[PDB]
Image (cartoon, rainbow, N blue to C red):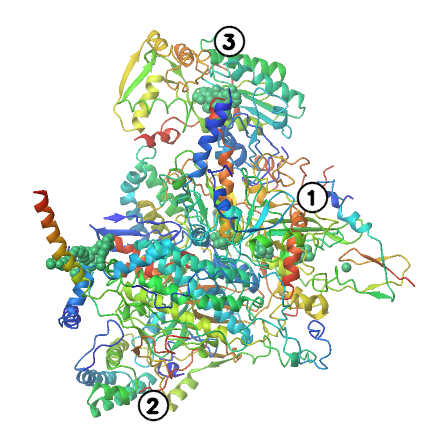
Amino acid sequence: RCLPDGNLLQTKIHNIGATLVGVDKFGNKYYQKLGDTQYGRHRWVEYASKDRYNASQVPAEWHGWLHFITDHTGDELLSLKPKRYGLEHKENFSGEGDAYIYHSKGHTLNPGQKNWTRYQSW
Amino acid sequence: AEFVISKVDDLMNWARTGSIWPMTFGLACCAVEMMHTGAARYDLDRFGIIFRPSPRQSDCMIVAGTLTNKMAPALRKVYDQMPEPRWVISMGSCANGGGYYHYSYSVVRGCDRIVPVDIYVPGCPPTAEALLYGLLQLQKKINRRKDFLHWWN
Amino acid sequence: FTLNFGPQHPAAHGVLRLVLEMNGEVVERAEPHIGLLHRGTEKLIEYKTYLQALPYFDRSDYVSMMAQEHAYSLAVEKLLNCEVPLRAQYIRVLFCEITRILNHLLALTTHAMDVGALTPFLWAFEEREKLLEFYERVSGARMHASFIRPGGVAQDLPLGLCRDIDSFTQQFASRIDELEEMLTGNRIWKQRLVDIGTVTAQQAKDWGFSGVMLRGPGVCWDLRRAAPYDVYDQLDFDVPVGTRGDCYDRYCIRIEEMRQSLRIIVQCLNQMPSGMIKADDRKLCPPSRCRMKLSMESSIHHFELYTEGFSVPASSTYTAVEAPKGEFGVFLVSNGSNRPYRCKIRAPGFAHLQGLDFMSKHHMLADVVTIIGTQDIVFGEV
Amino acid sequence: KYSWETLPKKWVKKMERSEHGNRFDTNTDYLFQLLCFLKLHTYTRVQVLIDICGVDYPSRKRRFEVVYNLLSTRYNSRIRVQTSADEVTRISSVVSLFPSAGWWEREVWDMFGVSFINHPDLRRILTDYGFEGHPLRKDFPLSGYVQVRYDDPEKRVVSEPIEMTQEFRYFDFASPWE
Amino acid sequence: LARKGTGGRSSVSGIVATVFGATGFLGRYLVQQLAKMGSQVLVPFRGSEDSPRHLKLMGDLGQVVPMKFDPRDEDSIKAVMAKANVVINLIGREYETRNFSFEDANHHIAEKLALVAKEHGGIMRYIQVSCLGASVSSPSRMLRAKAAAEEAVLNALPEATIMRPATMIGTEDRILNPWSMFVKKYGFLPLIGGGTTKFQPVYVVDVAAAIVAALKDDGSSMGKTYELGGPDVFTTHELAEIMYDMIREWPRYVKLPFPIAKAMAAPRDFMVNKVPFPLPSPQIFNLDQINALTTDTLVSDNALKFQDLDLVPHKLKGYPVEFLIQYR
Amino acid sequence: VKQTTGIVGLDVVPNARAVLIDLYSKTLKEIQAVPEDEGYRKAVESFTRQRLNVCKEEEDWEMIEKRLGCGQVEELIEEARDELTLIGKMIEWDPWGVPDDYECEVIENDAPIPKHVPQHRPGPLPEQF
Amino acid sequence: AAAAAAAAAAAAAAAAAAAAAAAA
Amino acid sequence: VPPNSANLTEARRRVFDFFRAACRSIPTIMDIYNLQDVVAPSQLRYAISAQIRNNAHITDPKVIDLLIFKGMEELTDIVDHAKQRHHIIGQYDFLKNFYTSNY
Amino acid sequence: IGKVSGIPEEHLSRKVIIYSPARTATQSGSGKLGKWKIN
Amino acid sequence: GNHTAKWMQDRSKKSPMELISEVPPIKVDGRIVACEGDTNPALGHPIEFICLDLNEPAICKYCGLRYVQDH
Amino acid sequence: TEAMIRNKPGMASVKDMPLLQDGPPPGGFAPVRYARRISNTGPSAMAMFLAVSGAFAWGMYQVGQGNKIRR
Amino acid sequence: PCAHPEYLEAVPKATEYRLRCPATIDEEAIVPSSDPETVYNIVYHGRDQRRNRPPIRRYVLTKDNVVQMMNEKKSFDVSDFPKVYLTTVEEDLDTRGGGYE
Amino acid sequence: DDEEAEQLAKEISKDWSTVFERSMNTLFLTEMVRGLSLTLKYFFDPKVTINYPFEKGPLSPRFRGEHALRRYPTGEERCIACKLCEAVCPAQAITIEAEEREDGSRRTTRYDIDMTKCIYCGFCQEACPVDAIVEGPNFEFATETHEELLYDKEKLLENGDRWETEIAENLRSESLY
Ligand SMILES: CCCCCCCCCCCCCCCCCC(=O)O[C@@H](COC(=O)CCCCCCCCCCCCCCC)COP(=O)(O)OCCN
Ligand SMILES: NC(=O)C1=CN([C@@H]2O[C@H](COP(=O)(O)OP(=O)(O)OC[C@H]3O[C@@H](n4cnc5c(N)ncnc54)[C@H](OP(=O)(O)O)[C@@H]3O)[C@@H](O)[C@H]2O)C=CC1
Ligand code: SF4
Ligand code: SF4
Ligand code: SF4
Ligand SMILES: [Zn+2]
C-alpha cells in the first residue's frame, strides 16, 4: 500500500474479496472478483510498478483476458504464444528518450537514416 | 542539495498532472467518444480532468474530429489564449494526422499544422479508454517536465 | 445588435457558430455558419469504390452511426438489385434501431445538458456505453462500425449477442423511465421547453424537416411507415406524433421513439431467421475467408471486390431511410464504373439547422441552445 | 403517372424517367415554374424540397445538372425534377416556394458554381471564407489548389499557401469487359 | 543543395540545419524560413521540452527535429551535429546568468560549436550570429564576447558566414516588448542616454531571410561578415515614437543620464554572488545593454549590407511592428 | 364539432363545408381561363367537380371526409386554396400548348429494385373509416 | 419588447401514436 | 440577381455599378482592416480598376455577370470581418528560371 | 470560363495533352477505351 | 539478406528469409501438396497446390515452406 | 465448396448443413416492457398539505410554548 | 414513491452479463454463406442481379405524340388520381400488447 | 386562438379537489421531489465507473485497434505483397513497395501504414488474403510525436509478433465468421 496519492487505492480497495488469477512475467498481478457485483469491474490488473505504471504494460497473453475479449488467463495462452518469432512486450516507450521511442527510417534520429531517392546517383 | 529541487519539481508536476483541465475542442465524433471518456464509465473527473468550456483557464486542449480549413483559424485563436503551461492532445485520426480526409481540400492534414501537439490519441474512433490512455500519457509528459531544475539551469 | 454565439459547451455541439442578430435578449434572427465541419465527404466519395465509400457514412452522423450505412447500403442495393437475406434485414434493423436508441439517448440528454440537467447526460451515456458493447462486439469499432455493407451486412452476430441485447432490452424501459421521470415532470423542464421552437406543420414541411421535427408538428410521416425499407413492414411499432410542435413535444417523441425502438429491438431479437448473412451474389458480397481461400472462383471475387468493387450499373436513385436525426437520404448518381459519381448526401441538420432562423425568432438568447438541442444538430452531416 | 398528364408538356421539356424514382428533367427556364406546379396543386402536393443535388457531367455541354428532389408528404411519393445549367448560367431559385432551398442552393453554388436567380443571400456556405474554386466539380482536384493552412511568423494567423502533400494515389481498378 | 521539390513544406533543400538558437526570438523566424523552404532543421533545445514545441509545426513531419543537448558538454553537440550540413549559431545572451557567464554563453560556446563542427567534416556552411557593432573594445561585455566569438569562429573555421544583425524588432522581441509593458507604467518610457543613440533595427523576418539567403547563395557569403542593419537609421527616442503610434498611448518619455541608469542597473549585476537565487532577467535596465547604448556604433559601415544578398529589408512602420497592436 | 386537426397550424374550421363550396365554385369559375385541351384543365375540372359535388350532397364535415376520402376538410381547404393560387398563377406565364420541336425523351429503365429497399408503398385506401 | 413570450401553458400530455396501432 | 445581360451593354452597366460600389466602399475597407496608412485611396482604386481591366476582354455577357458576382462576394467578405487583413495588404529571363528548376 | 472557375492563374497556363488511353496491352479487353482524358 | 536489409534495421532478430530457409522441407506422398497454411485451412493462405516432379524442393510461394516428393 | 466448409460428417446431401448461428432461444425471449411504469404511489395532495398544515398547526404552537419558556 | 413499481427492479448493474466472453469459442458458429440449393448449382445468369435487367428504353416524344395523348385523355375520372396517404393521429397510452413487447 | 386554447386548457382542470391537487403539486414540489428522490437512489447505488489503468472496458475479438502484420508460425512474414489492403484502404494509409527477395518468394520491401491517415475500419484485415495484416486489440499506442505514429515499413507492424498470442486467439475465435 502506502500510496494515498493514487487511484491505486481504488484497486487495493478491490482485491478484498477478489481471487488472484495468475501473474505474468513483468509482475502484474491479474485479479478476478466475479459473482459479487458490478460487471465490467470483475477483472483488473495490479501493475507491480506502483509508481510509473501505465496501460499497455499488460502483455498480449493477458490483454485478452483483461479486456473481457476472451476467458483464457495468460497462463493458458502462454502455451499458444509462438516460440520461433515470439517477442516480449515493450511498455510503449512513447517520449521516454530517443532510442526507446520508435523512429521511421528517415527521421535523422534513427541510426541508419535511409535515403529514398529511387535513382542511384553516379 | 539538488534533492530539494527534485522534490519541488515532483510537486509542481504532481499538481499539473493531477488537475489538468482541457478545453475540449470536441469537433465531430471523437467529441462523442471524448464525451464517453467524460461519461460515467471512464471518468475523466476522476483523474482531475475537468472539461472546461472556455479557452481562458485550461491546461490542455483535446482537439478531436476533422480540423476543417475553416476551423483552423478558430482553433489557433483558441490555442493562443491558453495559459502558458498548456498542452494539446490530438484525438482521432482526423485531428492527429490527415486521417480519412487527408486528401480532402477543406481538411488540414492534422492539427499539427495549427497547434503544436504533445500527445496524439491514436485510432480514428479511439476507444474511450484509448483517449483516456492518451491523457495518462499527457500525465507522463507532465511528470517529465522538471521546470524548476531548468529554471535553475 | 450582432452576437457571435459559438459553441456554448464544446464536445457536445462542436463547431456551432451561429451569428445571432439580437434585440436585447430577444433574438431577431439566427444566422448559422456552416463549413467548420465541412470535410470533403461529397467529393472524397467520388474518388473511392462503393466499399471504400461506406466508412464515410458512419462518419456523416457521429451520434447515430449505422443508420447512414443503412441508408447508403440501401442506395447501392436500389441500383444493384441486390436482394439481401432475411437475417441481414433483421440484423440491419436491430442495429438501425439500436442506433435510433443510441442517438436519442445522446440527442436527448446532450440537449438536456445544454438546458442544464447534468445527470441525464451521464445516465444516458452509461446506456450508450452498453450499446457500444454491441456495436464494438458485432463489428469492432465502438462508434464507426463499418458493418452494414451494401450486400447484406459485414459479418454475422457473435454467438452471444442476442442474449446480451435481450438482457439489455429488459432493463432499458427503466432507463427511459428515469430519463423521463427526471425531465418530463420537471416544471423547470417544461418551462424551458414548452412553446419553445414551435413549428407549425406548414413550416416543418416547407423547410424540409422530415424527422422528429416533422412529427412534432403533427404530420404523421415516418419513412418506416411510409416507405418500409426492411422488415419494418413486418415489425409492429407506433410512430409517436406530436400535437403542438414545441420543443417539449419533440422531446416527448424522442423519449417515446426510444421506446418504440425498444419494441423493434425486442421483435428483431425474437424473430431473427437463421439464414445467410450476406447476399448470395458473390459478385456484390465478398466471399467469406474460409471460401475464398478454398475456392479459386471465390478468391477471384474477393480480389475484384476488395480492389475493383461492384461497378453498380448506371442509374441515379434517392434512397432515404428514417435516420434518428430525420430523413437521411443519399442521392447516389452512379456512373457504370466501380466508383460512385456525385454521391450526394441529403442529411437532416442541413435542413433542420435552416429552421433555426425561424424557430428561434423572438425566443430568448438562452433558448437558442434549446432549439439547437431539439434539432439534434450534428455538424458532421452539415 | 398522373403528374405527367396534367403538367404542361413544355415544362417537362427534355427527359422523363420511370424507375429508381421518377424524374422530370426539365429546362432551367421552366424550372421554378415547374416547381410551382407539383406544389400548391390538389392532386400533386409535394410541399417538401428534400434535396438539391448538383451533379457535374464534364463531358456534357450543359455541365452541371441541378437535381431537385421533392417529397410529397400528402400522396406519399417522391419526384426528382432536374435541370441543366453550365458554369455561367444563372438558374431560377426555388427558395420562394420551398424555403429550405436557401441553404441547398447556397451549397450548390459553393460546390459547383450554378448561381441562383433572385436567391436572397447567395453566399458560399460550406467552403472556406476566402475559398476560390468550386470543389464538387470534376476538374477540381481532390487535394484542392491552395488549401494547406499552417501557422507561421504571421502569428495568430494560418496562411493559405499553395498545397503539397503525400500524392493522392489514384488506383485504376476499373477493369475491361466492364 | 540536393533540392528535390517545388516550394517548401514538403520539398527538400539538402539543408539539414542545426539552428543552435532556434528556441529563441530570432530562432523561430529562421527555423520557419529553413523549414518552409523545405529543409530539415535539427533544432537543439537546452532545457524544458516545451521550448521548441512551437517549432514542431512549421516543418513537415521530421523537417524539424527538436533535440536535447547540454551547452557545456560536447559529445552531445557532436550528436546534434551528427547528420547536418548547415550549422547556424543563434546561442547568445544579453544578460549574465549565475550559471553561464557572458563568455560562456556568447564566445566560449560559438568557439566550441565551431570546433566541434570543424571536427565533423561536412558542415558546408556554418553561419555565426553576433550583434552589429560587436567589435572588441566595445563597452558592453556582451559585444566584446560576441566579437571574440566571431574571431574564434572564423579562425577555428574559415569560410563561415557571420551575420551581424543590429537590435532585431518583431513579435516576442527583447527591444520593443520591454518598452511596452513599461509604458504600462502609465506611459512612462525611460529612454536612456537621452535618445542620442543611433542604432539601425531590422525586422527579424528580414534577418532570418538574410541568414537563409547566405545558405541558398553560392560559394560566396563564406567568411564574409555581413552587417544585417536594416533601413531607416533610427534613434532610441525616434523608435519609441513609432511604438506609441501602434499602441494607442501618449508619448510621455523621460531622459535618464547614463550614471543614473548604471546605478539603477547596479543591482542584477551581482549575478555571480546571489547563488541560491536566480535573478529575473533584466529586461529594460541592463548595465551591459546600457554600455552598448552609450556609443552609437550600432550603424552599418561600408561592410556588407542586405544589398549583397539580393535582399532589401522591410521598414519598421506598419506590419513589421504590428505586433504592438496586442498592447492597445 | 371537430376538436382539432392533429396537424399544428392547420386550425380547425367550423364552417368547413361552406368555405369548401365557395373555394370549389371559385375554382370551377377560374379554371375556364385555361385552354380546354390541356390535361391540367381536365384534371382540375374533374376533381373539383367531384369534391364540390360531395360537399354539396353531404352536410357534416365528417361525412365529407368519409365519402371524399382525402384526409381532413381543413387539409382539403388547404388543397383547394393552393389550387386557386395555381390557377391564378398558371393564367400568368401561360405554359399551355406544345412548341413545334417538342423533343421530350421518355426514358424507361425497368431494372427491378430489390423489395427490401425504400419503396414508397401506397398506404391505406379510403376505407380507413 | 412586444416579442411573443413563451407561454408555458398547453394541453395535457396524451401520447399520440399513429392510426396504425392494430390494423394499419 | 437575374442575368439581365442579354447583351454586353447591360453587363458593362452593372460592371460600372459594381465598380462604383467597391470605390464608394473603400472607406470601410480602409477602416475595418487598417490600410489608410499603408495604402492610398488612389492605390486601392488603381487595384480595383486593374482587376476590372485585367478581365475586360470577355466577349461573353454571362461570364462577366459571374465575374461581377465573384467580385461582389470578395467585397462583401472584405467589408465585414469575414476574411482577415494580412491578405488585403497583399491584394492591394529564361536563364533565371533554368537555374532554379526544370519546369 | 477559366477566370470564373476559381482555378489559380498559374494553373491556367498549364499545357495539357488530350489523349484517349490506349488499351492495357496486358489484358485483351476493350472496356476502358473511348474515354478521352485530359493529361 | 539485402532485400530484408531494406525494411529491417534491427539485424539482431533472425531475418524472416532465414527463419524460413532453416525449416526442413516436408516429406509427402503424392505429386501435389496442399500447404493450406499453418494448420487451419481458414487461418492460412489460399490453398496452393505445389508440384513435386522436380528433385529439388518446391517452395510454397505464399508461406515459404518447402515440399519434397519422398518416394 | 460450401459443402467442405460446413462438414457435419455424413448428411448425405447438400441440405442439412450445420447452420449454427446466433439467434433467440427456442420460445423467444421474455416479454420485454416498453411502457412507462412510473408508480404514483406517494403522498397524495392531501396528507402532504395536511402534513405541512398539521406541522404548522402543532409546530407553531410549539414555537409559541418555546417563546413562553424563553420569556 | 417514485418510478419503482416492482419494474425498475430491472436495474442497470447486471453482474451476470456477457457470461461467455466473446473470443471464447464454446460453440463454433457456422454462419451459412449460400443457400443449400445454390451450392452445387452455380448457374449465375439466372441468379444475376447486377446485369440481369431490362435495358434502358429511351424513346423520344414529338409534338404529334403528346397532342395525340392529350386528345386521348378525355376525362380524369376518379382512380386516375393519386391516392392520398391517409394518416390520422390517435391517442394511446400503453394498449399495444399491454406495455409488454 | 391561443387565448381560447388557454381558456379551455384551464377550464379542463376546474373542479375543486382537482384545482387542489394541481395547486399542491405546484405549492409543494411533487414532480421535483420525484427528481430528487431518483437522484438520491442513484447517489447511493453502486457506481458504473472503471478505474482505468488497472481495469479496462470490455472489448471483442473483432475489436479494431493497432494494426499488426502477422507472421506464419515458422517465421516468414505472412505479407505476400498483393497490395489488396493498399487498394482497399479508404484513407490510403498503407504504402506497399514489393521486391522478389533473394529466396525468390515475393515480399514487401516497404509496408508502411500511416496510423494518423488511417480510419481503423478493418478493411485491410478483410482484404488481406492470408490474414497478413490484422488489427491487434492494442488501441493503447498514443505517441508523443506524429512521426512515431506513422508505422514504419514492416518493422513496427512486425511488433505484432508480441501481440500474436492475442491476435492468434482472436483470429481462431473470429474465423468462424
Ligand atoms: C413534499 C415536500 C417538498 C419539499 C421540497 C424540497 C426542495 C428543496 C430544494 C429545491 C427544490 C427545487 C427548486 C426549484 C425552484 C423552482 C420552484 C418554483 O418556483 O416552483 C413554483 C413555485 O413553488 C414554490 O414557490 C415552492 C415554495 C413552497 C412554499 C409554500 C407553498 C405554500 C405553502 C402552504 C402552507 C399550508 C399551511 C399554511 C396555513 C395553515 C413556481 O411555479 P411554476 O412556474 O413551477 O408553476 C406554476 C406557475 N404559475
Ligand atoms: N535580441 C536582439 O535584439 C538581438 C539579438 N541578436 C543575437 O541574435 C541571436 C538570437 O537572438 P534571440 O533569439 O533573441 O536571443 P535569446 O536571448 O532569446 O536566445 C536565443 C537562443 O539562445 C539560446 N541560448 C542563449 N544562451 C544560451 C546558453 N548559455 N546555453 C544554451 N543556449 C543558450 C537560447 O536557449 P534558451 O531559450 O533555452 O535559453 C535560445 O535558444 C543571439 O546571438 C543574439 O545575441 C542580435 C541582435 C540583437
Ligand atoms: S478521426 Fe475518425 S473518429 Fe475521429 S473525428 Fe475523424 S472520422 Fe471521426
Ligand atoms: S483500417 Fe486498414 S484499410 Fe482501413 S484505413 Fe486503416 S489501414 Fe487502411
Ligand atoms: S497485408 Fe494482406 S493485402 Fe496487404 S500486401 Fe500483405 S497479404 Fe496483401
Ligand atoms: Zn504455404
Query: Is residue C163 rendered to the left or right of residue M95?
Result: left
Name the residue: 69% across, 52% down: A81
Please state the chain letter of the residue tagged with numbered disc 1 in the rendered image. Answer: A
Query: Is residue B121 rendered to the left or right of residue M99?
Result: left
User: Distance from label 1 to label 2 (Cα)?
Assistant: 77 Å
Is disc 3 surrounded by few (<14), some (14 to 19) or many (20+) residues within 10 Å? some
Q: Which of E239 and C183 is in front in this view?
A: C183
Residue identified by numbered label 3: E136
Q: In this view, does C47 lie above or below C262?
A: above
Q: Quadrant of residue J38?
A: bottom right
Q: Do labels 1 and 2 share a chain?
A: no
Q: Is residue C53 above or below residue E141?
A: below
Residue type at mark 3: give it. Answer: Val
Q: In which quarter of the image is ligand 1?
A: bottom left
Residue identified by numbered label 2: L78
Q: Does the residue labelled 3 lie within 8 Å of ligand 2?
A: no
Residue type at mark 2: give it. Answer: Val
Residue type at mark 1: give it. Answer: Arg
Percent coordinates x, y for residue A108 in the rendering: 63, 35
Q: Are marks 2 and 3 in contact (CB under 8 Å)?
A: no
User: Distance from label 1 to label 3 (Cα)?
Assistant: 52 Å
Kindly state the secondary structure of the residue where label 1 is placed.
loop
Kindly state the secondary structure of the residue where label 2 is placed.
loop
Q: In this view, does H101 lie above or below K2?
A: above
Please state the chain letter of the residue tagged with numbered disc 3 in the rendered image. Answer: E
Residue identified by numbered label 1: A118
Q: Do the residues labelled 1 and 3 touch (CB within 8 Å)?
A: no
Whether residue G2 can be seen here: no
Please state the chain letter of the residue tagged with numbered disc 2 in the rendered image. Answer: L
Percent coordinates x, y for residue C246 in the rendering: 27, 65
Percent coordinates x, y for residue C207 in the rendering: 32, 66
